[PDB]
Image 1 (tube, rainbow over the protein chains, first blue to last red):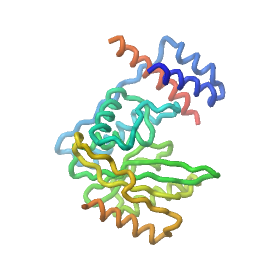
Image 2: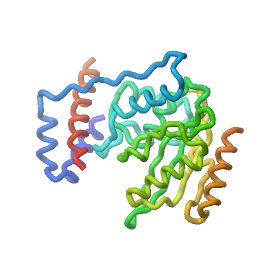
Image 3: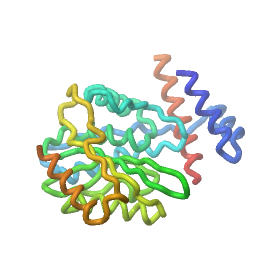
Length: 234
Length: 24
């Protein structure tokens, strides 16, 4: 894949202040810091699922957020689960920086071994300064409590330990986090539970419920998140 | 293995670039 490769370097030349010298120095450097390949977390059966989730999120963090502007693992959201799981395995083998969508697939791959853990995508549409912004994380449920795995440029727009007692509190935490960086939350897309079968021929349902956060209002927004939580226990 | 020695150097370069791009 040489075409893509030189595409990434030309795009860096534009956006960075000293675009050209940066590519020269890095591509031409004979000695670079060797990056250790992150070890895939494997768990004893005695380890509680919350402690497992911290290790999965730590592994996801080690890969780092992809700031290069070029995505290394393209994801067709309509692919069957067994196709995305093959792709997650290759992220595991390539071990490259990632963005929001790739971390959701990794979170599913690494939590398929936890049948007591429910996983479901949560994507957000936010508004700021005339522009729209889309982000997505992996919602998780353990022992009746809610949390999230994901990848973001902000610390409070990804990992939440499974401590929220309702889905509303989890989502409103994200809305509050969006508000702290002056983003208005326009729309929330919540998916259905993801099968734990890594060979499953079914798609992820990214849009089982679409909530218009402005046209709904506070309490009607809360009732909709509670209906979605009720729906995942189907 | 010519494929494999190429992915390791590319990975070192991607993370070198990724570090610079985190200046924001």
